[PDB]
Length: 108
Ligand SMILES: [Zn+2]
Image 1 (cartoon, rainbow, N blue to C red):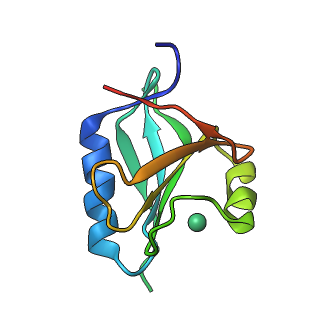
Image 2 (image 1 turned 180 degrees about the vertical axis):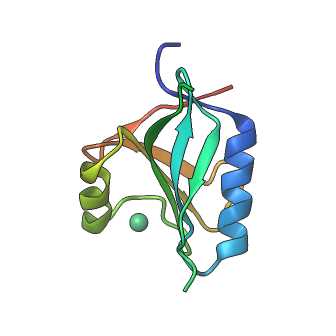
Image 3 (image 1 turned 45 degrees about the vertical axis):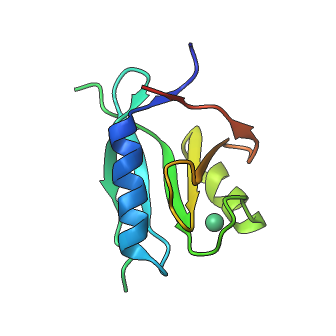
C-alpha cells in the first residue's frame, strides 16, 4: 500500500522495550527512511534520509487508546504515533495521526 509502514522487527523491539519498562511508560521517537518505520530514537523515560515519523509510548494498563494528554503530545511533532499496551502481545498496539485518529500501518 501507500500508507506508512513499520517493520515487524521494530514492532518486536518496541513491544519488548515496553515489557522491560513495565510498569513505567516506555517512550521513543519513530524513525527511518523512505516510508518505513524501522529505527528508534531512544528517550530517557527512566527516572542520510533519516526522518522522525512521530512517537511511540506504552501504557501499563490494558488500554491502547489515547488520552487527552496523548493528543497534546501527538500534535507537537510527528505524523504518526503508536501506543502499545499491557500485556504487550504481538497485537497490543495501535497507531494514530497527529490529530489522535486511528490510522493503519502496513507491517512489512
Ligand atoms: Zn498515553
